[PDB]
Image (cartoon, rainbow, N blue to C red):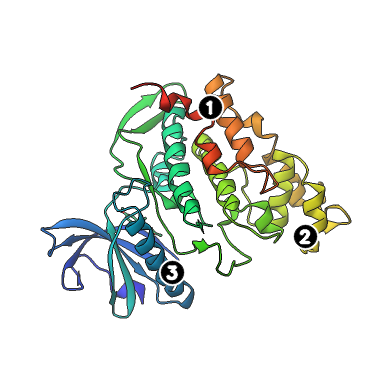
Amino acid sequence: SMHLICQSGDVLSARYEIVDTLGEGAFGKVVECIDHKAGGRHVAVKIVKNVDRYCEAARSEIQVLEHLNTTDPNSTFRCVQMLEWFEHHGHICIVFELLGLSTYDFIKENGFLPFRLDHIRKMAYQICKSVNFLHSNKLTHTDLKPENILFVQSDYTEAYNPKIKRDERTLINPDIKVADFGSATYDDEHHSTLVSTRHYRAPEVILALGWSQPCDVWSIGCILIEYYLGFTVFPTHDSKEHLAMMERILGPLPKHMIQKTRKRKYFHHDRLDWDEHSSAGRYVSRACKPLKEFMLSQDVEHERLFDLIQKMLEYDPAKRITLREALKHPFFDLLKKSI
Ligand SMILES: CCN1/C(=C/C(C)=O)Sc2ccc(OC)cc21
């Protein structure tokens, strides 16, 4: 399938000439192309793996992007713009505007160093604005992560930082768009039990208590921590271990969530079925600690970021801050000071 249809100099749909690879995943591959029928404009083309699950996701993504791009033709709310779609050797191919590196790939190529706070503020504001627009449209993204947040243009300057003894890349312009609408779900359509990538998954999702727009707010909180530290505070590939890290970082789960959950496999009576002295138990207590102990400074702007993160990681999904409320949080006041 994929390896065999996607090399430099291939022309797709009689107009798109491949010149470079932008990204690969289990989903397929994104290539950079010259569009010979739009005056040589460069575009991105996603070539989707010919596998039921990713075929079904691509067809759902095309329907979501047609709606979102028509509703917001000026891209005021910063969703990726889809130009068209076609089929190539029976693979679904989606054409987009050409953007820059994903926030994940930038962090990777910067030796997993974090962003400076001023970029995190601008990036956080734009992400909340974009995903609030989806929420206004009775949609939930469900899979927000640093790989799905794209820079518009990833040009950088580089200098030695003697503070950390590391060469460091800084963006010229940190402006972002949101991508990857393949899992996005309307209020009135069927809700899968399993949504989100492990490290960004909300507690109501893990405990199968029903989910909606607030599971996107949890994901965004986890994204801001990774932007701030350069690593996840949930380094795990196990549902119960994840819950144990949550309790160490954020405090005990609310009693009403433990007693409603059908996920009895995680629990012994009314508490997590957890051995603090096992291999996983030792790891969790070495690797995890109270959230505010991860702060790198006590400056007020650091306190303002950590107050927003704490609100976004409220366990109860009704109590949890909405993105409409988040855009008014004091961390963003610096962005709104007169021009
Ligand atoms: C590789 C990221 N990527 C996408 C990924 C998915 C899963 O859809 S969609 C997309 C559009 C433009 C782009 O330009 C560089 C990149 C781009």
Q: Residue at x 45, y 71 (%)?
A: 54
Q: Which quadrant of the view contains residue 67?
A: bottom left
Secondary structure, mark 1, is helix
Residue depicted at x 46% and y 21%: 163
Horizontal side of 271 relative to 131 (left or right) equals right
Q: Quadrant of the N terminus?
A: bottom left
Between 152 and 116, the one lying in front of the other is 152
CA distance separating discs 1 and 2:
35 Å
Query: Which one is earlier in the sequence, the residue at label 1 or at label 3?
Result: 3
Q: Amino acid at mark 2?
A: Thr
* Vertical side of 172 occupied by 12: above or below: below
The residue wearing badge 2 is: 261
Residue 49 in the image: above or below residue 46:
below
Provide residue 165's location: percent of width, then percent of height.
44, 26
Question: Mark 1 sits on what residue?
Answer: 330
Residue at left offset 77%, top offset 53%:
257
- Residue 236 percent location from the top left of the image: 63, 52
Give the amino acid type for the residue marked by disc 1 in the picture.
Pro
Residue 135 as seen in the image, left or right of residue 161: right
Q: Residue furthest left?
A: 39
Q: Is residue 181 visible?
A: yes
**Regarding ligand 1, which quadrant of the image does it lie in?**
bottom left
Q: Which residue position holds label 3?
A: 60
Residue 248 image point, x, y percent: 73, 40
Q: Does residue 199 show up?
A: no
- Gap between marks 1 and 3 measured at Cα: 37 Å
1 and 3 marks in contact (CB < 8 Å): no
Q: Image quadrant of residue 151?
A: top left
